[PDB]
Length: 186
Length: 186
Ligand code: HEM
Ligand code: HEM
Ligand SMILES: *[C@@H]1O[C@H](CO)[C@@H](O[C@@H]2O[C@H](CO)[C@@H](O[C@@H]3O[C@H](CO)[C@@H](O)[C@H](O)[C@@H]3O)[C@H](O)[C@H]2NC(C)=O)[C@H](O)[C@H]1NC(C)=O
Ligand SMILES: *[C@@H]1O[C@H](CO)[C@@H](O[C@@H]2O[C@H](CO)[C@@H](O[C@@H]3O[C@H](CO)[C@@H](O)[C@H](O)[C@@H]3O)[C@H](O)[C@H]2NC(C)=O)[C@H](O)[C@H]1NC(C)=O
Image (cartoon, rainbow over all chains, first blue to last red):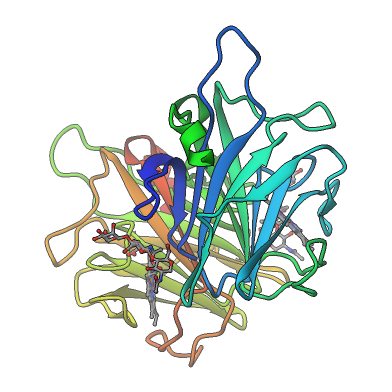
């Protein structure tokens, strides 16, 4: 599948991403302005907009399950629980051992039909194995879905069962940068 | 997703299609030679190679659930049960009333781990609603998956529940024809 640009109707944030029509989960990404005289930033802002039957969602930032930074999140009541994780094989991803900061932004909403996680991901484009994403080029992102609750929803490091679906989408990161990035943070 | 050309390693048939990595079902299509002179053929050969946990599979020949010819099939023991269907709104597709003949070809194989349905679809590029597929152009195909058994597996017109997954792929019909099509038939 292929990402495209879209606007959050509540916030007006402008993202690049997709809506999976099966689970009707929206995934959106936006990056700071491209630098020419300095190295690129290592942070980005993203969103997951998920129907409440979505019990956990994961994002694979390198487009595959293994050896890339993963983001995992779920609703637990009126709060999002989230974590940065990693998998070396096809088994339970565990806490990421590098430096990465996931911040839930206040635009994050939970209501009766959907949870909407809006986050800041710092240190998420370069990983502690030397891998990462190139925000000036084209890449692939992937997502994981489950409709089964995590084993212990109040724990960010909870274990859980294999996703019931997963998918991919191509993204041209060179088009996903925004001059309004700073304002989104504010 | 995008289709590519591949060869069936047992039969040697050359198909254009994809493998869905979630349910590990392969969808392949091959068309008779394009005509330079006159109307195109209205038939094609296809295959579904599915793990036996796949309880029913559907193919949407127009790339959508509604207003296009649908093919539905499942394993019932050591036989494939299949039918042509049509959907009026997002409800249980019913028997197609147009001109289309679905034939199970002798290459069809069912074993302990997979069912491989190889079929001939005559009259399937033009539908009795006046719609159809343009075999000289680029189009979209879709598939539907369930891991739950149909309500009556011995009935080709069995009712069944909503698919648990569905997906799409782009296909360049202009490169999906084969000079060996007639040999596939004999
Ligand atoms: C206990 C939890 C997990 C288990 C046991 C697991 C298991 C697996 C297995 C067996 C596959 C191969 C499926 C196929 O190709 O047929 C797979 C693929 C995949 N998994 Fe997971 N997974 C889990 C958690 C996660 C999480 C949390 C994410 C994302 C944050 C994820 C993302 C992926 C992706 C995107 C793929 C497809 C691409 C690939 O083959 O690398 N998985 N997983
Ligand atoms: C009793 C059986 C069925 C029911 C109740 C049903 C229901 C639905 C529903 C509600 C959707 C919309 C999903 C969404 O976008 O979230 C849909 C989508 C779709 N269905 Fe079905 N379906 C059934 C059988 C089939 C069959 C047999 C096929 C193919 C042979 C099929 C192909 C598709 C496809 C391709 C889509 C996505 C594209 C589009 O929205 O038309 N469905 N179905
Ligand atoms: C619970 O959260 C969800 C997700 O944010 C809310 O649904 C979203 O609500 C917005 C605002 O109405 C929808 O945007 C609107 O879209 C329509 C259709 O094009 C357009 O006519 C409006 O002008 C506006 O742009 C958005 O589509 C919708 N998203 C989803 C996934 O449902 C929902 O409203 C929240 N529930 C409550 C009770 O507040
Ligand atoms: C039941 O039928 C399925 C589908 O035909 C069998 O799986 C298929 O087995 C063939 C081998 O005859 C595989 O082709 C081989 O692939 C390997 C690796 O790519 C290659 O080295 C060989 O030269 C040959 O091309 C094919 O990949 C495989 N397809 C799938 C979807 O698994 C299955 O083995 C049969 N089961 C039993 C118990 O007979």
